[PDB]
Each structure stands twice: as C-alpha cells, then as structure tokens.
Image (cartoon, rainbow, N blue to C red; front, top):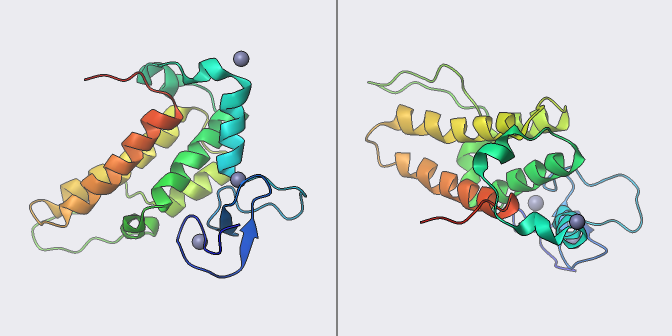
Length: 178
Ligand SMILES: [Zn+2]
Ligand SMILES: [Zn+2]
Ligand SMILES: [Zn+2]
C-alpha cells in the first residue's frame, strides 16, 4: 500500500485498501472508513466493481436523465466518489468549511454552501435524487463567482468547478460532445 492518504497526500493514521494499493485517513475516505470489514475495499475499488458487473453502464448518458435518478445505493456511491474526487484537489480547502461574507461592494449569497455540508447531507441520506447533490455542488462555485466579482480569487471557483464537472462526466458516463 501507499504510505500517504490518497485524498490529502499526507501521512498519518492510514487505513489500507485490500484490493488496491491506496490508503486513507479515516475521514478523508467517503464514506468514513468502516469500523470492521476484513477485507476492506476503498470507494475506488467499489466503483470499478460496478463498472465490471455492468460494462454497458459506461455507454454515454444524457445529463438530464442522470440528474433525475433516484439515490439508490449505486447512485449514492457514485456521488460519494464524485465528492471525494473534489476533496482530492488541494484547492478544495477554500470550499470545505462554512464561509462568511464581509467584502466592500459585495453581498453574501442567499444560500451558502460548502463541501462539508454536502458531505453531511450525503451521510444523512438527505438527497433523494442525483439532482439534489449536483445542484448543491454547483451552488458552491456559483456563490463564489458571484461574491468575488472581479477579484482574481474568482478563478479558484472556476478551477475547482472544472474538477467537479470532469469527474461528473467520467463517473456518470455522460455522452461525450463538442
Ligand atoms: Zn487524508
Ligand atoms: Zn481500493
Ligand atoms: Zn449488466
């Protein structure tokens, strides 16, 4: 196994996957690394199994159909994995914890949103459709763009949104377009 967390790239108290060489901090894995379970298989491994069980699941999909899917166990897992892929980028730090807004010439968003809030909402099974999760995720970046206006810090929201969107298209096998 690797000697650093796959998500935050630091050493520490690491749980090792039994079916691949990745390792994780307890609360860096999503869901949090399960108490017992020997062998244990990471989310990466669980996602790859879904694909292997149903090879046709990789054929292209329309975004509108994916959003309307109910949050059954496989879709729950795919959203957890997508959330984890965003935490994998170090720029996710800016979006992880609860924000506050006090900048001359700007007003805070009407509905603040942040990664740890989405993480708790997934854990608490608060989303009934993929659309709920995706809407909260895109709201994080949209709030940031609107609040920061012409400050160059706006770019951090474009960057992390791009990570989200690329992973969304990969995980949910969105039909490729120009
Ligand atoms: Zn970690
Ligand atoms: Zn694994
Ligand atoms: Zn099948």
